Each structure stands twice: as C-alpha cells, then as structure tokens.
Image 1 (cartoon, rainbow over the protein chains, first blue to last red):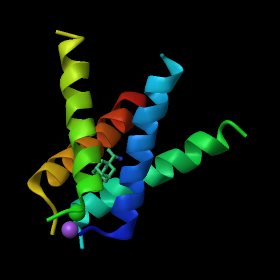
Image 2 (tube, helix red, strand yellow; image 1 turned 135 degrees about the horizontal axis):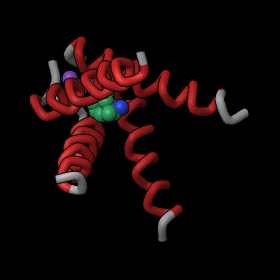
Image 3 (spheres, protein in one colour; image 1 turned 90 degrees about the vertical axis):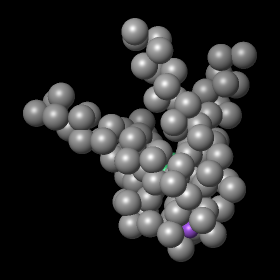
Image 4 (cartoon, rainbow over the protein chains, first blue to last red; image 1 turned 180 degrees about the vertical axis):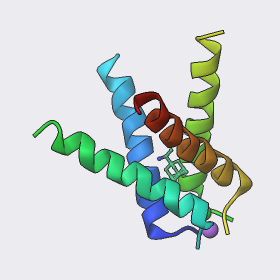
Length: 25
Length: 25
Length: 25
Length: 25
Ligand SMILES: C[C@H](N)[C@]12C[C@H]3C[C@H](C[C@H](C3)C1)C2
Ligand SMILES: [Cl-]
Ligand code: NA
C-alpha cells in the first residue's frame, strides 16, 4: 500500500515514461 | 501508507507536473 | 511495503539515474 | 512505510530537486 498521493505521482512518472517513448518511436 | 520522504518526493513530482503545464498554457 | 505501481515507478527513476550517469561517464 | 526501493527513488528525486535549485542560485 501507498499514500494515494504517492500512487498518483507514480502514475505521472509511468505515463511520463510512456510518452517519452511514444514521442521517440 | 508511505514513508514521509516518499510523500514529499511525491508532492515534488506532482507540483513539477503542475508547473510544467502552467508554463506551457 | 508499497503498491506495485509505486515500485515500478521507483525502478524507472533509479534506472533513469543509472542511464543518465552512464551516458556521461 | 515504503519499499526501500521506493525510499531510494524518493531520495534521488529530492536530491535532484536540491541540486537543480543549487545550480540556479
Ligand atoms: C520520481 C517520481 N516523481 C516518483 C513518483 C513517486 C513518488 C517518488 C518515488 C517514486 C514514486 C518516483 C517520486
Ligand atoms: Cl509506499
Ligand atoms: Na506503503
């Protein structure tokens, strides 16, 4: 378990990774 | 729950997203 | 403990640091 | 509580913020 704030920041970072990849594909 | 250091790093990443957006609006 | 999404985002950030270092050595 | 990996990534993120601030002061 995690603070919902920590989960959201985690989803930002993962989505940041996704898009970084997609912009470079 | 989360360690308070993880919460603070979370709040930094969220605020970082906020400001990144604001500077681009 | 942490939520696996938080763990995954963590591994991204650590791996990001590693790569940033390696690209600059 | 958090996974030590989450704590580690959190410290990276907080130290990244600090350095970012210091390089711009
Ligand atoms: C570096 C990210 N902003 C991150 C987001 C979440 C909070 C902390 C640790 C990890 C999960 C990674 C900071
Ligand atoms: Cl956590
Ligand atoms: Na936790």
